[PDB]
Image: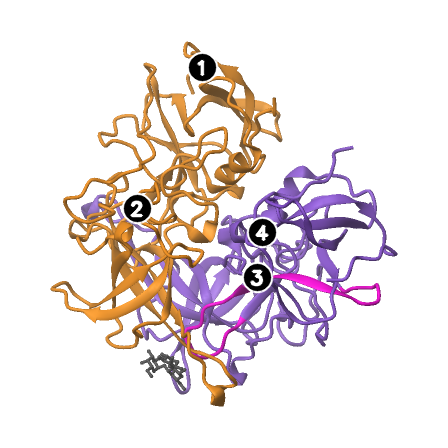
Chain colours: A purple, B orange
Amino acid sequence: SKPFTLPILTLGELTNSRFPLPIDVLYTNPNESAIVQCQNGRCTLDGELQGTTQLLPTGICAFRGKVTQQVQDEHRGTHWNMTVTNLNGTPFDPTEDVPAPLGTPDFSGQIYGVISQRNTNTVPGEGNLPANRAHEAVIATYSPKFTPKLGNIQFSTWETQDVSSGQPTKFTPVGLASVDANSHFDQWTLPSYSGALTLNMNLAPSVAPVFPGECLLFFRSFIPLKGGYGNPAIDCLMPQEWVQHLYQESAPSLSDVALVRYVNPETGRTLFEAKLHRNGFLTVARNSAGPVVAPTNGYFRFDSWVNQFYTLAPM
Amino acid sequence: SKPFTLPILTLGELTNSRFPLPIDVLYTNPNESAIVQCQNGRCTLDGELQGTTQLLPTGICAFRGKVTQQVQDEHRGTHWNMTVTNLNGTPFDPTEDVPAPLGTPDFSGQIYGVISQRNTNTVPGEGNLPANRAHEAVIATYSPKFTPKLGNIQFSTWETQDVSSGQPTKFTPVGLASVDANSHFDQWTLPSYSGALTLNMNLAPSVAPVFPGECLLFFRSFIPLKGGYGNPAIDCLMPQEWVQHLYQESAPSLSDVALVRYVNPETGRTLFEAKLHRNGFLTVARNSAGPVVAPTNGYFRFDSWVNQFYTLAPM
Ligand SMILES: CC(=O)N[C@H]1[C@@H](O[C@H]2[C@@H](O)[C@@H](CO)O[C@@H](O)[C@@H]2O[C@@H]2O[C@@H](C)[C@@H](O)[C@@H](O)[C@@H]2O)O[C@H](CO)[C@H](O)[C@@H]1O
């Protein structure tokens, strides 16, 4: 077969697969009460992308489409209805066996970013060039108007008027607007991709430890905020570079569980070991929550294929 | 000898190494009069990063640092000085043999994006959490105040007051503010990294065809605009995924030129051939400017190492 490998990129050379951020730390939270079932950063060890996962770092939490309607807020701000396409610009076919267009955000929150437009029509007197505009925007993924699987979403602006209808529109994500209670930030709560009364479909499966004393290991990034108090984070199961690597290699999985070692390349010693599961997630034997304190030169190296009964050395 | 390879990611699966954008099209411009000497997306075929190149898609045209104070400036908007560090947070050492902190923009223009801050100090009443803010911002890289090699740059905001002194600060690039004449957009004009009148140092070398009938081949992306007319583009020599791949493989270069073929896998046929040069750039035999019209599912396949005499089939 084709032997299994991971990239040799270090922690400071990896990026988050659920938001466009660098990886900051490795992280555990054994007492997590939520089901973990994120939809971006999902890839099996033999290279099958799942959920809404696509390969571009620029596509994570991105949208493309056109604005169709302006609707003022009751109190403050303006909302804009947007039809969405696939990120490559082709029409999104809701019968496609995916939860939503690839790259769609996979958590509840107010996602802050920039909406930009480049008009289709050009002006001969301007050298056959189009008009443009961009503004700060927020997409509330818990909104009843957040229906990307039906091909449409809503975003809000503080801008009151300068958003054009019928013109190509791009959303570049930047961070969150708020993590106040009213902003419903919960990184493990999936949006209702078709609206509140409708079941999500075609999901990548939930992940969990199955061996006693094990917990999930995450690649954690801190996410910027537009305002208010907080130090919010987004935890992914594998960095985007691992998704890209696994997709290209398509190495056969020889068992359900690979043993991997986090190594310090200077010393060559194993700092700790982890189980890398077939569905594309890590567990470790750790009985505590918080960051993993590790040498900056550390990375994961594949050791061998094991099974669910393998006992990891405690962290 | 570790065999040289390229990723099998397709054009719609690649991103630009000079700005955080997807690759839109392959592109030539044989009569370009400028010297081509970009500093991001620079990597030799045997995996040596050059210029200001680093590995993170999130690091391209990003800055990290601290705002010092608001500063006076004749130009429109409110202006702020910020110290800059390495992207990993360590102090930037100007004695390092690099032109500027890795990730620094490599072109003249008004770069539009978002400045965000997460305060160092936390508040007990807020659950021991820090205050945050973010605002749109512009960095004019041709400004005499743009001195990233000296550890200091300036940015402007529309916001008049809500940027805090002495707090951790991130710049997330989004596009350009303008491409009007007065905004000095020129993708091949390097910033003066240490200020007006100082010579840049430690640069990746210029690149050019050296064979009659040949021209540079670029991976082109269109860049968003905050306002104004235009359809500006940023051309890179190799996409970021190629930089990431070459860096990791570190395969010995067996000649100065790798012959590659652009293949349509669905049909299995070669669309055209190109030379991939040791310093990390492509040439083709083409006598016109403009996009290359071909499926976005096409990709470059390494064929063989060739010598200084090899003649490319015309596109
Ligand atoms: C949307 C807007 O106009 N923002 C300005 C406003 O921001 C503050 C309000 O949004 C407020 C509503 O209760 O929430 C605050 O969180 C927010 O301020 C932001 O967060 C606080 C904790 C501080 O870090 C502020 O610096 C930050 O902006 O009001 C502020 C000034 O208080 C600014 O004008 C915002 O532009």
Under tag 2, what secondary structure?
loop
Give the spatial CA distance, label 3 vs label 2: 37 Å
Give the spatial CA distance, label 4 vs label 1: 37 Å
Question: Which numbered disc covers residue A240?
Answer: 4
Q: Is mark 4 within 8 Å of ligand 1?
A: no
Q: Are marks 4 and 2 on the same chain?
A: no
Residue at the location (58% across, 51% down)? A240
Tag 4 and tag 2, C-beta contact below 8 Å: no
Q: Residue pushed farthest left? A: B74
In the image, B109 versus A80, the foreground residue is B109
Residue denoted by label 2: B232
Q: Are marks 4 and 3 on the same chain?
A: yes
Amino acid type assigned to the residue bearing label 4 in the image: Gln
Q: Is mark 1 within 8 Å of ligand 1?
A: no
Chain designation of label 2? B
Q: Is mark 3 within 8 Å of ligand 1?
A: no
Residue denoted by label 1: B313
Q: Which residues are magenta?
A: A208-232
